Image (cartoon, rainbow over all chains, first blue to last red; front, side):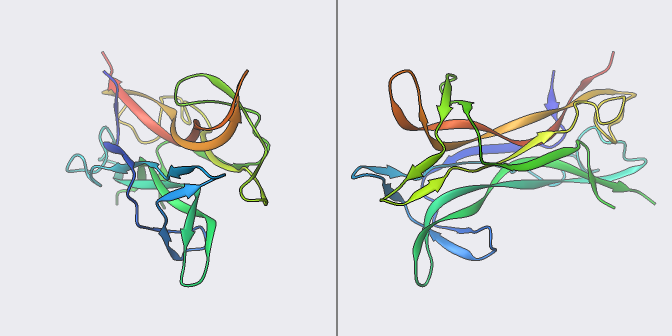
Length: 107
Length: 107
């Protein structure tokens, strides 16, 4: 049947406490946002790698005879209400969204 | 050097007009949100496949002798201000976030 090259794990996250923002700083993630007198809990759908090597040689199916590989998590950016040592603001934060295979040549 | 198995293309999108929501319906994406008397244009960072077959056999580096492959775009969910035939609301919409390789056995 069909299976990815890198095994992946997805979960809805409703209790996030810190995240790295687009500018690289660590920021605190607030839990509920009120947008116009009504509140929302902030949720993030994240997908992570289950393993950098789901198989001993790296990613599944790769041609190991020529290639080296491992799986790695890639990120999107989602704006969220956050706060830092001085200011609460909507900021863009890095969220984990996929597990992909990266290759290079064996020598 | 390091290269992905599936070639990928990322862009910030600031003029999105429709999106499919989590419930599957097509919805209209509004452009500016006012959260507390101040406005924001809504942006989405999307990553798409450049090709289902970046190489003639499917994804790069796969062992084609045993495997069939192609690249496919995976989605995250981002909440955005949207509207439908009756109601403007924050809804979760499907955003394209990665290009990953899917395998199956050749016979």
